[PDB]
Amino acid sequence: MSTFIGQLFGFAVIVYLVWRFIVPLVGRLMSARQDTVRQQLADAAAAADR
Amino acid sequence: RERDAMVAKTLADNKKSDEQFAAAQADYDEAMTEARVQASSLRDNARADGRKVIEDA
């Protein structure tokens, strides 16, 4: 039952690598898209009341 | 589909709003110039029949 521990260390380093490199950029991307559509709805309401 | 229709409706709303904005001053001037040409219709018919009565008297 020692391959379990080795694979678990492998899984730990791979999840550390993803949480370090990948999740920041994808978070930034989805946040940029979120704020873009937010601004779109906001100026839609603005043009309506205008 | 809804979001694209929304952005298109927003563009059209801005355009129509600015167009109605211009049409505001447009029709305001149109109405007041109709009014002043109606006014200038008077003060000449008055001058016309004033001249007529002055000459007939």
Image (cartoon, rainbow, N blue to C red):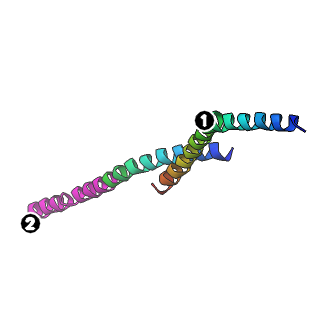
Q: Which amino acid is tagged 1?
A: Leu
User: Residue B52 magenta-drawn?
Assistant: yes
Q: Which amino acid is tagged 2?
A: Ala
Q: Horizontal and vertical percent for residue A19? A: 66, 39
Picture disc at residue B35 = none
Instruction: Tell me the crowding category of disc 2: few under 14, some 14 to 19, or many 20 or more residues within 10 angstroms, Cα based.
Output: few
Q: Residue at x 31, y 54 (%)?
A: B34
Q: Which residue is mark 1?
A: A25
Report in which chain the residue with disc 2 lies.
B
Instruction: Name the side, left or right, on which A6 lies relative to B21.
Output: right
Which range is magenta? B30-57
Examine the rendered structure and indicate whether residue B55 appears above or below residue A31: below
**Which tag is nearer the camera, tag 2 or tag 1?**
1
CA–CA distance between discs 2 and 1?
99 Å
Q: Which residue is mark 2?
A: B57
Task: Please tell me which residue lies in front, B23 or B5.
Answer: B5
User: Residue A3 magenta-drawn?
Assistant: no
Quadrant of the image containing the N terminus of chain B: top right
Q: Horizontal and vertical percent for residue A20? A: 62, 36
